[PDB]
Figure 1 (cartoon, rainbow over the protein chains, first blue to last red):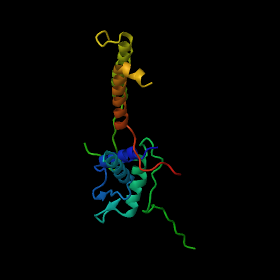
Figure 2 (figure 1 turned 30 degrees about the horizontal axis):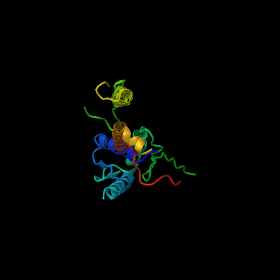
Figure 3 (figure 1 turned 180 degrees about the vertical axis):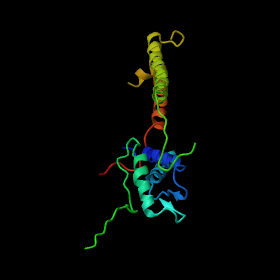
Figure 4 (figure 1 turned 90 degrees about the horizontal axis):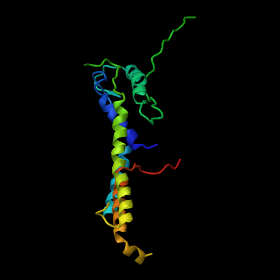
Length: 50
Length: 50
Length: 50
Length: 39
């Protein structure tokens, strides 16, 4: 399956769930594969344009 | 799941994870699994005196 | 409204699918006309008649 | 092949325009990824 849309949905849900968590608990992201995908896509698009 | 209040024990955080987020993040269309790492599993220990 | 620890809310209904279906149609109504126009221009070799 | 297309050039231009629009849409509505599935 596709990973970028899944990460997007996961982030949207974790964001809309921050209000339902108890007082003091935080969710910190550790590994996120969307960053590498975005960087690669941007690099290749810039290379094509150049 | 970090707690910058020294209030919620590790067992509370892991129970929250298991019984709330494993179900929240699993409804996403093509998420195969949501595994839990670390934390403590509450247990009812009965120690018998011989 | 406040949410208790371990509770979530979501929305759904028929409205969900319409927003999709309708959208898709607004993509294929133009295309159709296009593939019809190029049929008509080829037929009379003039834009006025089409 | 070549001269037979310069005769009816309006058809070719309209087809090229339709193709460009379709391709722009497909480009702006395509998935993305980093590397294919090597597993």
